Image: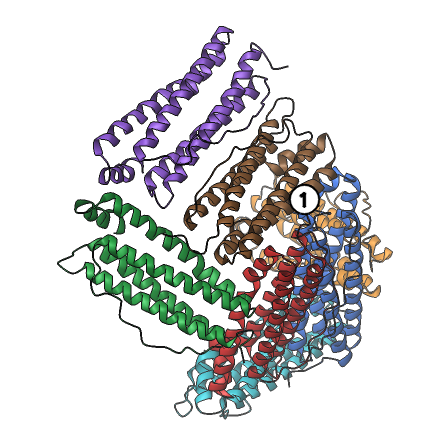
Chain colours: A blue, B red, C brown, D green, E cyan, F purple, G orange
Amino acid sequence: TIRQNYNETSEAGVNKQINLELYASYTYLSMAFYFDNTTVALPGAHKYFKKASDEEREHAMLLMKFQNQRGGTIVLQDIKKPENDSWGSLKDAVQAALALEKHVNQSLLDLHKLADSKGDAQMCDWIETHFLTEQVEAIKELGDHITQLTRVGFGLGEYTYDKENLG
Amino acid sequence: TIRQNYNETSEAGVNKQINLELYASYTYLSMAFYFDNTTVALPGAHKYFKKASDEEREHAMLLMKFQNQRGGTIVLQDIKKPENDSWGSLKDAVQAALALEKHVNQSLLDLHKLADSKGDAQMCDWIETHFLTEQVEAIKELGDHITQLTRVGFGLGEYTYDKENLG
Amino acid sequence: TIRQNYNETSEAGVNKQINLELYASYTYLSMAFYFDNTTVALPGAHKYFKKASDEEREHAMLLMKFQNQRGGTIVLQDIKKPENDSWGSLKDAVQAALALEKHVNQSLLDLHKLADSKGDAQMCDWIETHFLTEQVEAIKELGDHITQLTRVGFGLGEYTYDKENLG
Amino acid sequence: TIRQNYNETSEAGVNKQINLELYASYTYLSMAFYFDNTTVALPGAHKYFKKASDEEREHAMLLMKFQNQRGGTIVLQDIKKPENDSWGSLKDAVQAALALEKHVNQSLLDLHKLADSKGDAQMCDWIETHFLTEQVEAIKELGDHITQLTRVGFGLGEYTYDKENLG
Amino acid sequence: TIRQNYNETSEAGVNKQINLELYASYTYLSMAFYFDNTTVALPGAHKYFKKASDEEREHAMLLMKFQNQRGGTIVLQDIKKPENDSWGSLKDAVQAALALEKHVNQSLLDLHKLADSKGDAQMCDWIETHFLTEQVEAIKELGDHITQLTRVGFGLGEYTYDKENLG
Amino acid sequence: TIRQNYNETSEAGVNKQINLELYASYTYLSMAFYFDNTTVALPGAHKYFKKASDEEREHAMLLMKFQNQRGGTIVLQDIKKPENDSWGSLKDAVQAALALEKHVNQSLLDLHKLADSKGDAQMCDWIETHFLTEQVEAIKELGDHITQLTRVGFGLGEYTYDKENLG
Amino acid sequence: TIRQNYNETSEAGVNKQINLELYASYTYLSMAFYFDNTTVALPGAHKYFKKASDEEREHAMLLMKFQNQRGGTIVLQDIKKPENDSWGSLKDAVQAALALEKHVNQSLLDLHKLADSKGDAQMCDWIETHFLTEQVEAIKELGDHITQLTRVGFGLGEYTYDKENLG
């Protein structure tokens, strides 16, 4: 028996967070191929959101690994389809990505507070080390892109920022 | 308009195959991390079904890209959760994968037959080029794994084939 | 006698397609040197359409080679002058290139359907392998350029896309 | 079970084409060592037809492999002895090979036609990918050798082509 | 004076954990040379448990270093002799080590809990950074070895795992 | 305005020479693939007249570029099909090419005489620099090929000079 | 808005710590150039406290960056001048630095306790990661320098430790 100091509601929250990072993986994939659509056509954003979808999928597998290491049982649910089919302008899509990563951050903070309430020192530091500082950086990066996309405006600017920054 | 000789029924099956390949990616991920579970503990299979999950995910993006190249529209649906939570013995899982890649093959074949009936020569060759011959080889490999897993038996055999073959 | 399973109307269609790809070679050359004209002056487009004229000329020689390999007889006709003398804005010229490559695609699809009706398995796969997927990619690429040229607008944008993309 | 969309008359055709490609291997061997005979003594042809024998033997193994991938059963038959013991002039032997690869081509086309009649999309592409275009090129090459061997005539010319071309 | 926010019961706990990590070092040494004994003769395990002994001895020195950095006083005690003289089957010994690192884990958690109760933020992170996550991975690894050693069974299997895995 | 000392009659002859060089490119292409025809089968000449077609096409773009550099306007006309469909013997074709490059020379000479009569010093040197001395060498080479093709005779000779000289 | 789980009192302490670390940078600079003064003349310490000034300045920018990453607002205040103009003996200065890094530690600890009380898990780990364990090591090093400076005495000793240790 490897399980030690690993609460059962902790275990249930990791199962949830796994679903959330998969849901995020699938939302970014939806964005990536929206900018590959011929009537949108921003290759840099295609690149940028494909990698994002790769990363939160890593997130999920890092949480899957942690579940096994602590001695719990992975339990999967349906990954729900993304909230939209099309994503508007390049600025609109980065605003949704900001809203999405803030939603993920809040869950990671709730999981941390949960783990903390049950005295799980290791699960706290694991979440601090793999997710919390990286979320903070993800959020600040998106925040800067939104300021920039507003600064360059529409038309020529949207093209330029796609190519020269997101790619 | 880039759309040419691309039938709306073909477009809908593509979306249907995007969901299917994503479904297979999510099943393999389930298996991969079942073999990482401490009570199962087969690192070779864990490695083997993790790559398999990557492949059918690559399959989905290859279809997403093709939907865009032909001037269609991606429409995503939920990714249903895997049929099982645990996957039994190493031989039991390889059988489970054989049944899945056959299901996907029949689906890819029906999608070919649909495309052919609408006169879509390029779609036919594209499915032939990227999917039909790969499925044949994938099924043949699963079959040989099943035969070899039966030859090596349970216990020491299952270990050996895990490390030496799938690893 | 090398001729085997090679229909006489097939042979007549290859002779036609040779003329069409030459006509396309000559249209792109007309575009390439229109952007080299001092009152137009977009060097990137000059590059971009010179290479296009090189490529459909390869197309012709690939069809000439196939004619000989199958045992037919190449028969040449006049290459007709391009439909226009000047080609308008950079966006206007890429729209004509989209119309031209769709016209070529349709002929390649008609030749395929023709070859198919006469049971010519090899000529079908030859057309699938050298022309059909490449046409699909050519069309999607042009489609994206047209979206982008509309996005960046006129003046500064037209210059920027010429230099940073087409060159 | 791995067999899927693999019809029993297709499987019987595959067994017939393994025998024919082995039969062709054995004719080419016969010729290659005819030219090694001291009353003939054409070292270039020996080397050329030895290689062609390796070639159609690789064909046979390629088909045996395909039979196993689809879940068929290889069933072998006697390989009949070549039609002749000696092969006349070098030009006579190249004409014998042209006739032979045309027979193989027709047989390969009939196998495709049967595969297509049962809706075996994958079998059709496999034959297209590995055999149909390679047969066209081999036939054209033999055709060009026959024209060239007529051009150089007999005596000194036959010597020259053997050494400078077939070697 | 360098001591700062370093409480006396924390300092006493550090002295207790130096003894325990030295005790663990000395158990692993006992096992490693049990497997070197000619009636046992498992060279992989000898090498694996020798290294684990070096390991928990590095742990001890890491803690002695920490005691000095905070301005504590190292106070050493006898290292008790391991609980057994011989360690049964290889699987028996891996079970003995699992039990041992769990004891160390619980002790390490209690030390964290005490450090946190006195508000020693730095002591908590130090234990998180150097010990807590490493203990989880060691426990999971021992757990996986125990499942695998059951899988290969006794006799030939025990031989194989010793050489191919622990070595 | 960049146009200086560039007479309108000179401008029109340039367009007339663009057509002529394109006409020569299309003739050589016709010859090149006549020698690739299985009943003719002279790979050396095929290679030789393919390069020749590339050269006079380079000639046309060199004239197109010069029309633009002097501030004129390209006006394209049809490219007439080659005078013959087949080209007889290897010697017969080299004679056909000699007659063509002489025609092109007289045309280039008349274009020089026209430019000189209008006082266009730069155009004169440009034609001298890029065309007059190249035509002299091209004609001299064709002449030597004709003399050598007559020396080597028909049959074996024609083969030999094809492979060893034009190849 | 990027601001999430970032309390306004935490924001104000960050600004307060930016000032403190800048204050320490300006103190070390004062010391560094006291040891460069001709009547003091200890190049090793000059080098040692110049680097120390660089470090706590790096500390301030690391806090400035963190204020921005969390969506707060930098507010700068005066940097007060160092407590002394001269710094006495080499041992006297190292004691002065030990008192300063302890002051900064208590400040960093209170900032941690403040962040923890407002539930800011990421801020806590960030301070742990970048500051708490570095301060422990910095204080331990100053302590050892003080002990060594007392062992080597005044005069020749002070020289020796300056060049051989701080240099």
Q: Determine whether, in the image, residue F34 is placed left or right of residue G113.
A: left
On the image, the x and y values in percent for residue E126 come to 66, 68
Total of numbered circles in the picture?
Answer: 1
Vertical side of B118 occupied by C51: above or below: above
Q: Image check: A104 left or right of E23?
A: right
Badge 1 is on which residue? C143
Location of the N terminus of chain A by quadrant is bottom right
As drawn, the residue found furthest toward the front would be C8
Q: Is residue B165 left or right of residue D31?
A: right
Residue flagged by tag 1: what amino acid is it? Answer: Gly
* Residue G79 visible from this viewpoint: no
Looking at the image, residue G138 sits to the left or right of residue G106; the answer is left
Nearer the observer, E142 or F38: F38
The local secondary structure at tag 1 comes to helix
Please identify the quarter of the rendering in which residue B10 is found.
bottom right
- Badge 1 crowding class, 10 Å Cα cut-off, few under 14, some 14 to 19, many 20 or more, is many
Q: Residue furthest left?
A: D39
> At x 20% / y 57%, what residue is drawn?
D88
Percent across and percent down for residue A95 are 80, 52
Residue A73 sits in which quadrant?
Answer: bottom right
Residue F118 lies, with reference to residue B135, above or below; the image says: above
Q: Name the residue nearer the viewer: F165 or E137.
A: F165
Disc 1: host chain = C
In the rendered image, residue C56, in percent from the top left (x then y), is placed at 53, 40
Q: Residue at x 53, y 38 (%)?
A: C19
Depth check, front residue: C18 or A33: C18
Which is nearer the eye, F145 or A74? Answer: F145
Residue A13 visible, this angle: yes
Q: Position of residue B52 (x, y in %)?
A: 58, 69
